[PDB]
Image (cartoon, coloured by chain):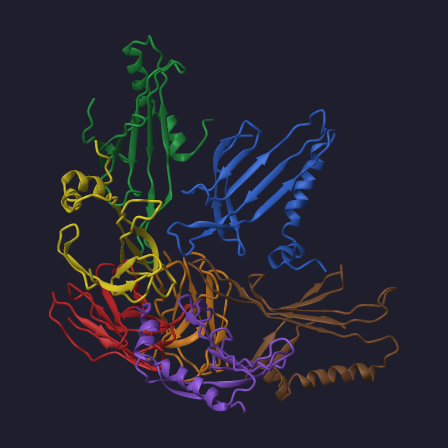
Chain colours: A orange, B red, C yellow, D green, E purple, F blue, G brown
């Protein structure tokens, strides 16, 4: 009914670069319904971006999602260590929810 | 405000299990409660959802006859039951609370693994 | 006679369920007694009334009357709790005259209680087929 | 003739589903017989009627008339059961005159039953395309 | 006297829950003081009013009046937007005359506060049974 | 000329989506041709009409007219079938006179198709900003 | 002067959230400028208007007027997207006369911007307590 594709699966880390992962739906998932979660290597996940625009409380200054339509993206500027573990994404349209494949 | 589930366990196949996560730090009958499966090598998906103040269960169509789940109002817990166990489900099972406008999940609990 | 907890047995399509009732006083406005099932919300419970009457200068006949209703409650989405959506009523009236003896009055009640279990009548009610 | 359990085979878009019906008596008010599918709730079941008529001093023609309706029910939204949303009626009326023989009356029925399977007519109904 | 945070203890069916109230000013239009529970949305909170009155050239009697209402919210539709399903009021009015002493005025209040805990009265309110 | 499956390419905000249409006959009542997207439910599909006209003794001018509507449907909470919610209409009318040549008639169509892609016009429609 | 992207900082109960606005042209019908938040659906976005006026032969006074509204979406029903449930209006009007200097006109604006942060006024708005 809706299928996600996160087009990178692996990434490299250097503390000065600007990295960006994207996702793409198979129909018109509306805006303000879809999110981003980061899960640590061995623990429960937690929220990162709600409604694709604003941020949660413990979020630092520099991560910012964007996109309108059916292909959305998260842009990281000035990445550092102890940042990248995993980044899932999920949306709710119609009824059953679905999560992303995963990236890192 | 938090919620904790259980410890690890194993059952031999063909049996059926109980799982639970008890809430604390808010009034119990006012928010939905979900359950989430994370098979470890792969992506993680959604299974069921109920409101404690009434009885209203909506379920995923892949796991339609697999899982039944209830909610006890006094002890403020939520029980989930599988059936016809096999080696297909061996994962950590989460439960998380939400309310409803932007549907997203507030507070995750620590996971409960399960082996067959 | 006197109100008490009227108990009932062997009720249903199979005749295995039971039902217990509790007295809830006599309305002195029109002589209508009442019984009820011990429920919580006062619009989601079964109730039974019964009220004898007496001949005035207008009516000149006794009139026993029994009413039964059974509300049905289901909870629609996004609503905290149960509501009432369909009810099934009932009615029984008797019209005995003044000089009637008691064997006749028992005979009418006996044949009504026997005729509510004949195969024609349960074919009529439980299947809504007209008698043909 | 006489009512019985009318069975039906090879019905559908593919022609593989079946359907069985049960008799539910003859209404003596207006001669309308009835058939029905063995359902539980009496507003969620398919039904078929048929009623011959006779010439009075006003109409002077026979009139056979057949009606079919098929309610469809969507599933529960809370827990309260199945409701009826749409309907799909049908109608067939015949108007044979007094001195008509039986070959003509069979011929009309035969060509109607054959013409309800021509490619033009299933192009008209199943796709809602006008005949052009 | 003077408004303050009126606290309350041993309230409920068991008598274990508590309730605290906060002052929210005196309306100078009609002398009606107010108390309230510290809630967020101003239509989902309990409130208590109290307003003494004075004899004019028309009424000639004092009149103390106390009102209580308790709305109950349903949050089925989502926490951000809850809708009040139903309400439950109260009312107490006193009508002391001009030359009344203070022992009488205390005696009426004392017997009302004692009579709201008799077994007849909690049989009347908590079960909706008429006194019979 | 003649109806056929009109295909379309590079349509959207990005210009990557496509759309295919199927002919659904000519209404002979008012000359209005029709096209449609191959959908299932006949109230959840896109459609395009086109209808030339001729000068009568009243109007004395040709009039080409094209209509487009796009219903978008989403299931509501109570229901189980998708339902239409909002609409999005369109309209194009031409009013060529009698002695007009064909270069003029092609020139109007060409400048309209070019002007529907200027930055002013997509600033006007896609953002609802007035031209200022 | 000239419209531009008006940015705003330290807004909220804590004073940490920000808000950015974009110009959306001047309506030439009644001189009302407009600003807006960069949203998608044109009924789910915050907007700010401002419109100076001039003395006619009827009114004889300048009149600056500022309006603010803030819709908040919620209540997604089913799977269709969100709709507006509440509003929150505002209004500021000034009525400077003809021979007024500019120190007075700055003084009124300065004391209004200072008085919207006094403890009495945030006690009045944020808690809905009347000033008493």
The residue nearer to you, when weighing G29 against B31, is B31
Q: Position of residue E63 (x, y in %)?
A: 54, 80
Residue A42 appears in the figure: no
Q: Is residue E14 left or right of residue F86?
A: left
Above or below — where is C2 with respect to B18?
Answer: above
Above or below — where is G46 with respect to E111?
Answer: above
Q: Is residue B83 left or right of residue F38?
A: left
Q: Position of residue B25 (x, y in %)?
A: 35, 82
Q: Quadrant of residue G96?
A: bottom right
Residue E74 appears in the figure: yes
Q: Quadrant of residue G53?
A: bottom right
Q: Position of residue G131 (x, y in %)?
A: 62, 84
Q: Residue at x 86, y 69 (%)?
A: G60
Q: Position of residue D60 (x, y in %)?
A: 38, 13
In the picture as drawn, the residue positioned furthest to the top comes out as D99
Q: Quadrant of residue G124?
A: bottom right
Q: Residue at x 54, y 56 (%)?
A: F13
The residue nearer to you, when weighing A68 against F43, is F43
Above or below — where is A64 with respect to D45?
Answer: below
């Amino acid at each position: 009914q809706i299928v996600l594709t996160q087009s990178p699966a692996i990434m490299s880390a250097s503390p000065g670069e600007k990295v960006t992962m994207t996702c793409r739906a198979s129909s018109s998932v509306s805006s303000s319904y879809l999110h981003w979660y980061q899960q640590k290597s061995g623990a429960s996940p937690k929220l990162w971006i709600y409604s694709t625009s604003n941020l949660a409380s413990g979020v630092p200054a520099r991560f910012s999602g964007s996109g309108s339509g059916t292909s959305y993206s998260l842009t990281i500027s000035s990445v550092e260590a102890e940042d990248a573990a995993t980044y899932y994404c999920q949306q709710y349209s119609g009824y059953p929810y679905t999560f992303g494949g995963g990236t890192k | 405000v938090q919620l904790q589930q259980s410890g690890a366990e194993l059952v031999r196949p063909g049996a059926s299990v109980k799982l639970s996560c008890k809430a604390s730090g808010y009034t119990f009958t006012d928010y939905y409660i979900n359950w989430v499966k994370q098979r470890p090598g792969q992506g993680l998906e959604w299974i069921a959802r109920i409101y404690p103040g009434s009885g209203n269960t909506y379920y995923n169509e892949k796991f339609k006859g697999k899982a039944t789940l209830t909610a006890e109002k006094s002890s403020s817990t939520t029980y989930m039951r599988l059936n016809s166990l096999t080696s297909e489900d061996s994962a950590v099972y989460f439960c998380a609370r939400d309310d409803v406008y932007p549907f997203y999940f507030d507070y995750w609990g620590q996971g409960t693994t399960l082996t067959v | 006679a006197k109100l008490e907890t009227v108990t009932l047995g062997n009720i249903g399509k199979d005749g295995k369920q039971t039902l217990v009732l509790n007295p809830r006083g006599v309305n002195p406005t029109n002589g209508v007694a009442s019984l009820s099932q011990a429920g919580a919300v006062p619009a989601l419970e079964k109730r039974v009334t019964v009220s004898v009457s007496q001949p005035s200068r207008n009516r000149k006949n006794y009139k026993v009357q029994v009413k039964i209703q059974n509300p049905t409650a289901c909870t629609a989405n996004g609503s905290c709790d149960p509501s009432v959506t369909r009810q099934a009523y009932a009615d029984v009236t008797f019209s005995f005259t003044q000089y009637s003896t008691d064997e006749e009055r028992a005979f009418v009640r006996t044949e009504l209680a026997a005729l509510l279990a004949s195969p024609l009548l349960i074919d009529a009610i439980d299947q809504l087929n007209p008698a043909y």
